[PDB]
Length: 187
Image (cartoon, rainbow, N blue to C red):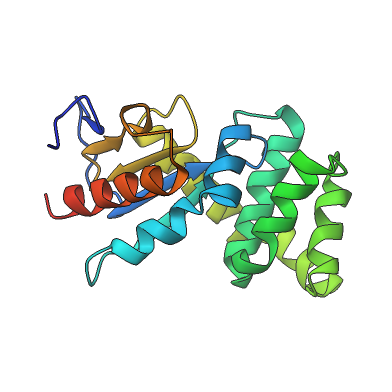
C-alpha cells in the first residue's frame, strides 16, 4: 500500500546524478540521534537494499551554528579516513547525551579516544581533500534544497516520509522505513 504522500513524497524537481540512497543528518539533531542510536535506521535500510545499491550519508551545516559547521568538517574527516564506524556513536553521545562536545577540540578528542592518531586527524582536518568532501556534502543538500533532517532520498526523485509510518512499535517503524527504501530503489 505504497502511496505518494504517505510513506514517501516525490520531488517536484528531480535531481540528476544523485547517489542511489542519500541520507542527511546532523549530530546536533535529536531526531537524528533517535534514528541512528535507537532505531539503527541506516543499518536496517542497508540490510534490505538490493544488490548494487550504495548508501551515502552526509552531515549538514544548518543546525548548531559554529559547531554544526565543525561537525560537517569532522564527518568529512571521518569519511576521508574511513572511520565513520568508530566515531558515529561517540559523536552522537558527546553532542547530545553527555553534551561534552562544545568546540572543535572536543570533536578532535573523540577521534583521539577512538584511536585516530592526532597527526592523522590534523592533516586530514586541514586538507583540501576534506574541504572538497565538505563541499560535496553541502552541494548534495543544495541539490534537493534540503530544509530538514533526518532526511533520506532515493534516486534523486523520492523523499522518505517517516510521519506516515507506525510509531507505536520501534521495530515495525524500522521495518516499514527499510521496506519503503527498497520499494523506491526498485523504482
